[PDB]
Length: 300
Length: 300
Image (cartoon, rainbow over all chains, first blue to last red):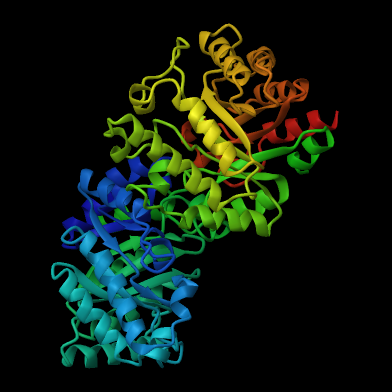
């Protein structure tokens, strides 16, 4: 059975997966995505270092391929991340003038979002903006522009494509007792009260064995920020225990504003941490017990 | 052991593999390439649709990543294909004016080769130029320019980077009686007699089970064209039988002008025909029997 069909039958929007051109032309990835998943994301083809490697020199061939494939095959598209320190080319980090950096950030956002206007359901606008202690991460945008870079990014994104859901994304939001989880909730509440158009919080979830249970309490906490949506992004789980995966799916089901889940690839050998075998399909493209456990859970 | 070190000890230049950025950051590909292979090729990041998706406007982020990684890790680099019909954006195929298409083709060749001047050992300049019956394939270049497009392409490439070895590449050159094999020999001899700088023939070798034996006769026939070099390119073998792979390696060893072999990826799940398990490593990144058979053949 298709986990995307089953999660839609329980009132959610999608079960999705990250992919890109050379996955779709190799292995069994295209066949599995067509049958079992409802939304694709670019693994890497939309990141800043892939799309604007030097100023004004936009590289769209890879992202175009993915968007086309998804439209032909009737899949939803999510994309990101527009502003994220980790995938930033050096030409951006070396800018020290505030007005320049604001315009460079705006141009990057507007150019990417305009190109795909109306085709992208969800955009990750700002990523990994918090330190582990809950303070704001001192990336180039915070250092040069200040804390208004976040309002500016979201305002710019809303103007570029008013149809898209705009998300802030972070990782290590997997425990309700962790300071970072509480901090992002408090800051998003205050940004939204001031009119910043943040539609969603996306939890980048790279879990160790046994950490699924904690998400049952972390996800409701993220939802308490009052955004229209929350989601689970680029999920994988070391060891791929059915218990961990089922717990994450049940957290999604329990939180009414959680629209769906995106796993971080199809088959284990194509994972960034392949030795931990953390995905739902094995190296022979066979479903693993965690896939069947999700199916069972969604049927009941 | 490393098959690249062992083939070097037998007097050849390399045992290589096709890869690209997202392979180097996932699975065990980087570790295996570092240990076992001596030359990397771009799986897709140098093709025309990836590098010049609109006229005069280039996308080099993916190719730059590969070239940098290879230099950092002491690997040789091969690249291609500059002029192929199968990877051509629609804007090129629509051109109907001979001078315009010549200029477009020359600009494509010169821009890519200049960017990496001196860094690339082998360039595939023209690919898949022949029909199965041995006549020239009627692609946009033949239809608009005529059969001079091949001389022009090679002369332009030689001027752009004199260091590089320049190859023509085709598939189904695997049997010595097949018409395409003799046809490429006939034409390459003619072109070289006219001073066209074709340094090599690359045989793009996608074999079915049992076809390795015929390569022992086909590869020397290709070498009879008199090019300085021949190579085996983008090799895979349905079923990955040790007998097939050993026969291909021995054909390389038997042909003095054959400089090396490149396989079409590391592990079976990342093959374009994964259900035929045609590569040297399995879905858990373990060497397969064919890998060990090549090791022993090269030591004996």
